[PDB]
Structure formats: structure tokens, C-alpha cells
Image (tube, rainbow over all chains, first blue to last red; front, top):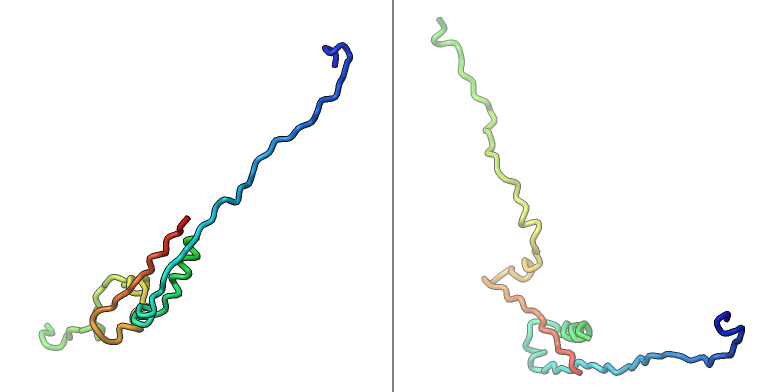
Length: 55
Length: 54
């Protein structure tokens, strides 16, 4: 304020910004064959849990 | 001297042999003893996970 004589004038304010882009879209997609579902030793629902764990 | 009337003595207990404490059969998994009631092989299978696609 002292170097300015004793003058003051008002500045314009401004902003910065960043974009959160929601640009990721990812998928799981697999077949459970009915012949395999019948012929295997037990439940295949562990593959639905594996798909969820992968995402 | 008493060549005939002084006994020799035996202990009635055998000394049992000193042997290692067994531990491993209590530490490993026993779950397949349910299925292994017959046959000479157990097959165990594991999941391969589905791949995430973009």
C-alpha cells in the first residue's frame, strides 16, 4: 500500500478447477455350460464370487 | 559267605524308549478324510477367475 503512493484499486477474483471424469466402465462376462454344470463334482458359484472379486 | 541266599532284584517296570513329540498331523489340514473313506486318489480342483474387460 506504501509503494502504491497510498492508492488501492479492486482486483477481479478468479477460480481454478479439475474434472472428475467417471470415464471407467469395466465388465465381467462368462458362460457356465449346462453340460459342465451337470458333469462337475460340485457348485460352480465360486466363479460368480471370482468375477465379483476381479472387479 | 552267602553264595546262595543274597538275591538279585529286577524292577517290575520296563524303561519306555524316549522319542520325539509328534506334531505335524495336528497342524496340517484333515478335511479330505471325509471324502477319502474309499479309493486311492483324491482330486482337488481350483477356480481360475474370469478376466475384467474394458
